[PDB]
Image: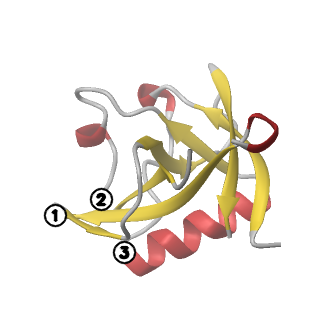
Amino acid sequence: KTHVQLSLPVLQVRDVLVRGFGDSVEEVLSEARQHLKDGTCGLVEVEKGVLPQLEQPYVFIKRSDAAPHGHVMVELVAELEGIQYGRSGETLGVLVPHVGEIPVAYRKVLLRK
């Protein structure tokens, strides 16, 4: 399927144990996609002070369209030293590995895969 319905655990930035997916734009997009498939991906909502507490390159989920079955359609955009790889809509948050942190909420998304 070109899209997959996912429910992403929303994590508080100070709880996150593994603060990024790797060391290159290509690696973080690769790893983000694998963790999304494996159900081991969390989401941190971006506010003042959040991104400096996470590791670059960043992987964002961005709204790709204006929401089947409650699921917002999203795609992945990476960012490294102020350059983004991908073009999409409004940021829903930054993806990180989930290794058992307790979430505050879930974010229903339809991921373009």
Residue 107 seen in this snapshot:
yes
Residue position marked by numbered label 1 in the rendering: 81
Residue labelled with disc 2: 56
Judging by the rendered image, the residue that carries numbered circle 3 is 25
> Is disc 1 in contact with disc 2, using a CB cutoff of under 8 Å?
yes
Label 1 vs label 3: CA separation?
Answer: 11 Å
- What type is the residue that disc 1 sits on? Glu
> In the displayed structure, would residue 80 be above or below residue 39?
below
Looking at the image, which residue is at 16% across and 63% down?
81
- In the image: residue 92, left or right of residue 37: left
User: Which circle, 1 or 2, is nearer the viewer?
Assistant: 1
- Direction from residue 16 to residue 100 in the image, left or right: right
- The N terminus lies in which quarter of the figure? bottom right
Q: Are marks 2 and 3 in contact (CB under 8 Å)?
A: no
Q: Give left or right: position of 85 versus 62.
A: left
Crowd class of label 2 (few under 14; some 14 to 19; many from 20; radius 10 Å): many
- Residue 34: x, y in percent? 67, 69
Q: CA distance from mark 1 to mark 2?
A: 8 Å
Mark toward the start of the polypeptide (2 vs 3): 3
Crowding at mark 1 (Cα within 10 Å: few <14, some 14-19, many 20+): few
Where in the figure is residue 31, as x and y percent of width and height? 57, 70
